[PDB]
Amino acid sequence: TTARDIMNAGVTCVGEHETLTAAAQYMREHDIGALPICGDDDRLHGMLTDRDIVIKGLAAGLDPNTATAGELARDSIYYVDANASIQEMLNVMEEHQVRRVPVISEHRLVGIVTEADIARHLP
Amino acid sequence: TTARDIMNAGVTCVGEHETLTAAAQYMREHDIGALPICGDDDRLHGMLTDRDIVIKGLAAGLDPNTATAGELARDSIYYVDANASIQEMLNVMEEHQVRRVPVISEHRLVGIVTEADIARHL
């Protein structure tokens, strides 16, 4: 089993220049706490979490209407290759203490894999 | 075992009129994701989470520098008495779907108990 086999494919990557307020809207829209952030051509720049917006954004004196997703997401760059094994995915999740990881193929975001996805497809 | 036995006593209740930006600063200071909010009467009004600020605040078109903790915490009221049992704490956590619960005694916030506190001291 590979990341490509269990990932949620076709997820939209939020632009690095989008504001934190805009990112907050996407999180409400999809009811999620982390968004993959990209530059041009679906190139992954990092992950932005809801807590990031509060702690690294609001609590750091940034204006959510001008501070960008990229400014905060560039602090968190982790991912797995589309051919990564379950063990590898868990390794990344463990090290970074996260429940979901971006999947990359040819430098482009191709999907997102969650810990729940792994639990569902072990057999 | 009671709530008073495993709670984090002496935590400060954030004022209902404090802004969301102020609330975020407190969450950073203590590295926590939820804050107990109290009114001018010192009575608990609710809990404000980091996600609440993002979803009920920013995503709802509110200005974090003007919207208040109290306006977002109003509909998130739950707690346990200081003499509450582990089962009671679990009932509140399960039913409200939360991991942090404020502890009250004589109508005053005396601490916060977490699921981790329970697991650790279980």
Image: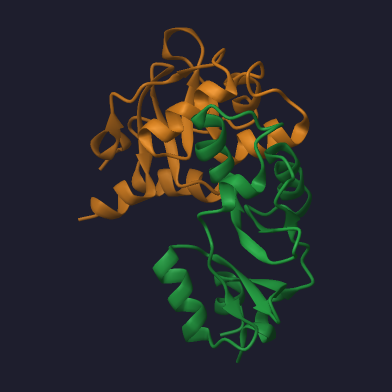
Chain colours: A orange, B green
Which residue does the image show at 62% across and 89% down from the upper left? B83
Between A73 and B76, the one nearer to me in the picture: B76
Which residue does the image show at 33% across and 25% down from the upper left? A11
Between A4 and B14, the one nearer to me in the picture: B14
| Relative to A69, B27 lies left or right | right
- Quarter holding the C terminus of chain B is bottom right
Which residue does the image show at 69% across and 67% down from the upper left? B43
- So how many labels did they put on this image? 0
| Relative to A76, A62 lies left or right | right
| Relative to A89, B6 lies left or right | right
Residue extending farthest top: A40
Between B24 and B69, the one nearer to me in the picture: B69
- Quarter holding the N terminus of chain B is bottom right
Residue B23, position as x, y percentages in the image: 71, 45
| Relative to B87, B2 lies left or right | right
Residue extending farthest front: B41
Residue B59, position as x, y percentages in the image: 50, 30
Residue B97, position as x, y percentages in the image: 43, 63
Residue extending farthest bottom: B1
**Residue B18 placement: quadrant:** top right
Residue extending farthest left: A123
Is residue A80 in view? no
Is residue B66 in view? yes
Which residue does the image show at 57% across and 30% down from the upper left? A77
